[PDB]
Amino acid sequence: RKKLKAVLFDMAGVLFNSMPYHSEAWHQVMKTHGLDLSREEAYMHEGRTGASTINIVFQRELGKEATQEEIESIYHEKSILFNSYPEAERMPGAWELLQKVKSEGLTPMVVTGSGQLSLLERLEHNFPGMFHKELMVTAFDVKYGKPNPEPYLMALKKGGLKADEAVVIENAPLGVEAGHKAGIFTIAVNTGPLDGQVLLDAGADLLFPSMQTLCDSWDTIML
Ligand SMILES: [Cl-]
Ligand SMILES: [Mg+2]
């Protein structure tokens, strides 16, 4: 890993344990609108923009595109369900891994589709001295969500990085696809209920069952 300069962290399900909340919120919001999106299906659709997930459900069952008004209202309803849960806490091992990454001289980057205000300071409270404004990719930076490679390509651009100078930590099949399509070595961390084979089919180079285990095996990963 002599060429390696940076580690590109997905947020949801990698830094913070937010996916029990996201997947239930999505299942429940659709169920209220007479629509069938299961929790496992929500997990399969992790990393998509709200506009993407809603369109998929709408085209499949109703035979229609979702309008912009219908997107914002369903996304806001889903946001209310999500926000009624106690704020997600840290993925065990993430802070320890970040410590190792930084001590190695590698640059910690964060990539997410979230449009949260006050994200940096939340990241600063939870992982002191790790992340920086100029080295963040969020919803305001990119148009598309996973499996589009654009967020990770933006992350390389902002870091001044080639594809071979970075690694992606992902937890989600569509996110893993985005990292692999961006030409970046992609490590999968299986923090949900899906089969590890689903992350492998998506293009994951390595596969670990938790963020702690990746941290423990970090100095035995070679590039
Ligand atoms: Cl999150
Ligand atoms: Mg994720």
Image (spheres, rainbow, N blue to C red):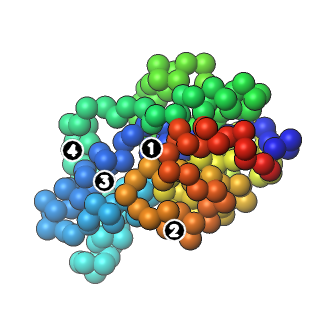
Residue lying at 55% horizontally and 18% vertically, measured from the top left: 128
Nearer-N-terminus badge (1/4):
1
Q: CA distance from mark 1 to mark 4?
A: 16 Å
Q: Residue beneath label 4, please?
A: 81
Residue 192 appears left or right of 67: right
Amino acid marked by disc 3: Ser
The answer to whether residue 132 of the structure is visible from this angle is no
Disc with the residue nearer the chain's start (2 vs 1):
1
Q: Which residue is mark 3?
A: 23
> Which residue is more in the foreground, 55 or 16?
16
Is label 2 or label 4 in front? 2
Choose between 211 and 177: the one closer to the eye: 211
- The three-letter amino acid code for the residue at tag 4 is Leu
Q: Which residue is mark 2?
A: 197
Q: Any atom of ligand 1 within 8 Å of the CB at mark 1? A: yes
* Marks 3 and 2 close (CB-CB < 8 Å): no
Q: Secondary structure at mark 1?
A: loop
**Which type of secondary structure does the marked residue at label 2 adopt?**
helix
**How many neighbours does mark 1 have within 10 angstroms: few (below 14), some (14-19), or many (20 or more)?**
many
Report if residue 36 is visible in the image: yes
Q: Which residue is mark 1?
A: 12
Q: Residue at x 71, y 55 (%)?
A: 184
Q: Are marks 2 and 4 in contact (CB under 8 Å)?
A: no
Left or right of 125? Residue 108 is: right
Which residue is pictured at 66% across the width and 60% down the height?
205
The tag earlier along the polypeptide, 3 or 4, is 3
Mark 3 Cα-neighbour bin, 10 Å: few <14, some 14–19, many ≥20: many
* Res. 203 image quadrant: bottom right
